[PDB]
Amino acid sequence: DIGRSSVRPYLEECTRRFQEMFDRHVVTRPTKVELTDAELREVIDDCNAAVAPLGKTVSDERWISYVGVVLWSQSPRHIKDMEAFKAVCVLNCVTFVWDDMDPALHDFGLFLPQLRKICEKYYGPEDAEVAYEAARAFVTSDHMFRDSPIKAALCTTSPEQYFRFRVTDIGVDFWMKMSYPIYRHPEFTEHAKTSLAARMTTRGLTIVNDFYSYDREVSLGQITNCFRLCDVSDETAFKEFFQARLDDMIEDIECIKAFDQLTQDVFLDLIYGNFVWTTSNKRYK
Amino acid sequence: DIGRSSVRPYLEECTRRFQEMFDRHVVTRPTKVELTDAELREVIDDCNAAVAPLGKTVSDERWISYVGVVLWSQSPRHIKDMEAFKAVCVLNCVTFVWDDMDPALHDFGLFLPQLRKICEKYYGPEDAEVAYEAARAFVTSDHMFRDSPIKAALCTTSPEQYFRFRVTDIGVDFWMKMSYPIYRHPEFTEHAKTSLAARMTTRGLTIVNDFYSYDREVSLGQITNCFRLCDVSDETAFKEFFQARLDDMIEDIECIKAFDQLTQDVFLDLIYGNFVWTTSNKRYK
Ligand SMILES: CC(C)=CCC/C(C)=C/CC/C(C)=C\CC/C(C)=C/CSP(=O)(O)OP(=O)(O)O
Ligand SMILES: CC(C)=CCC/C(C)=C/CC/C(C)=C\CC/C(C)=C\CSP(=O)(O)OP(=O)(O)O
Ligand SMILES: [Mg+2]
Ligand SMILES: [Mg+2]
């Protein structure tokens, strides 16, 4: 049954169709933000220190693996604050490590002050509180509402309810709220703070992530994946579902182009960058 | 054109159908929170002081009209903090007055510090920052993106995109982020802070407000109304659209019932309470 289901028959075609869609609708190719050796070392040092109180040891290779999503999904042309950039590198990486941990080993009393220390190092006083609150909310939500009936209801009812849940759960709201200081762009800053930024980009991020993590997630009993709403065994049902999802992505991209140029660049680089990172990364194979 | 269209032919039937839906799906009838004479006095005094720098003088009757949405839509069974309650009364009322003002007269330099003063009076340090940030975001969104292509794109594309804009624009995210301290309920606090609370309740709130404000908004050229997505002149198109909105509200209500009992009470009291207030208030006639 579902615990043994797979999208493996569709990997090649779906990858090519995602890329075809991005070339047509976004056009601008993702590029990688470059960090100097010293900047990368500072990020890795900060990640190791954040996760040290947890008794967790993590290799440089694994940190670099996680950080790629930041290097690829941010928008290099628009960056103004590289201190905020390194904070997102660190926040992103330590939250991945936390998520990959056995939940029985989550110690919020040790982890939250580390998240706060990161925010306070890299951001101004105002920004530090916004980014910390988003980080605290993400990690708290994950805990509070696992094995919750709410997750089951939202994830099994309809794509729309599912994506409503993923606005927070896939981490985009947190991403926006820690990323706006990178750009110092007034419009982007407000869209981030109202969460309209996250609401516009959630489907594009989530459909991609869900496709490439489905086999692993389903093998582990995890229900937070939109492809669980269709029978991935029936080639015909799958293809119809996948096309509806591509259509969702396209509608969002087309609406995103109504935003101001800088903001639209950042949103589209995020969705398209995430896909590039996702298909190159060992986490999803 | 659409500027002279009307849903007046449908008022009685739609009102009856909304009520029948709530009686079936929510069941628990809205009740009105009691303020003592002293408490209402305090609220009105605070309202007048906030809008005085704007040269605004407002009658008790007008303030009482605005505050009814708070007295009816909050959940009296679950109130724990009446200071937070009065803060919502004040914040709600002064935001109404701001929104009814000629935009040329909006003076953020004068108004924002008044919003901050209200939050600092009634909330603890942590809650004051969350409520104030949500008020600031709401009022800043309203300004920044008032004649924005984004608003047009979102409001005209699909119901989905429209409701995505209204999460912030109808003010529910702000409502949730100023209301959670009333209840001091951990789960509700978190759903408020992640905006999941707002995402679950926006369609119920927005569909009802939109129906009862359509005629006035369309006469003023305003585009923020879901009934603009159909031809309200065509009775069969309208009835089809209306049913689709009712189905949306019912789906949200049924998913809301998967939340913990206190949270679901609050969410449902809000949607149903707003309907009761909307149908009895002079603002929509
Ligand atoms: C915000 C953004 C750029 C993209 C959306 C997805 C993504 C790669 C997020 C990482 C960036 C952020 C803010 C937080 C990390 C949280 C996390 C472990 C997300 C994975 S989504 P799932 O729970 O499905 O885990 P899996 O990776 O195993 O599929
Ligand atoms: C936010 C909530 C719980 C319910 C929605 C109902 C409502 C009017 C709430 C006001 C309460 C809050 C937080 C803010 C005030 C915002 C405001 C003046 C109007 C929003 S509806 P539109 O912009 O269409 O104006 P109109 O009233 O003239 O139709
Ligand atoms: Mg996944
Ligand atoms: Mg209205």
Image (cartoon, coloured by chain):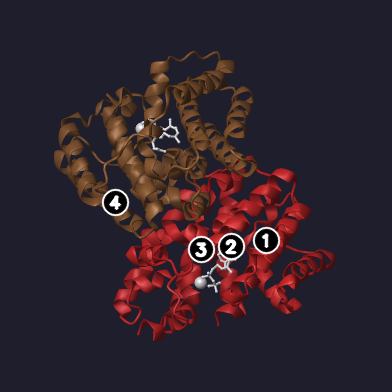
Chain colours: A brown, B red
Residue A270 image point, x, y percent = 36, 42
State yes or no: discs 4 and 3 in contact (Cβ < 8 Å).
no
Mark 3 falls on what kind of element? helix
**In the picture, residue A130 is in which quadrant?**
top right
Whether pointer 2 and pointer 4 mark residues with C-beta atoms closer than 8 Å, the reply is: no
The residue where tag 3 is placed is: B144
Chain holding disc 3:
B
Residue of label 1: B112
Q: Amino acid at mark 2?
A: Val
The answer to whether residue B48 is visible is yes
User: Would you call the spot at circle 3 few (<14 residues within 10 Å), some (14-19), or many (20 or more)?
Assistant: few
- The answer as to whether callout 4 falls within 8 Å of ligand 1 is no
Residue situated in front as seen by the camera: B234 or A197: A197
As measured in the structure, the alpha-carbon distance from the residue carrying label 1 to the one carrying label 3 is: 15 Å
**Which sits earlier in the primary sequence, circle 1 or circle 3?**
1
Spatial separation of the CA atoms under disc 4 and disc 1:
38 Å
**What residue is shown with label 2?**
B139
Residue nearest the observer in this picture, A278 or B266: A278
Q: Chain of mark 1?
A: B
Q: Secondary structure at mark 1?
A: helix
State the residue position of label 4.
A248
How packed mark 1 is, by other alpha carbons closer than 10 Å (few <14, some 14-19, many 20 or more), is some
Please name the amino acid that badge 4 sits on: Asp
Does ligand 2 reach within 8 Å of label 2's beta carbon? no
For discs 3 and 2, the disc positioned in front in the rendered view: 3
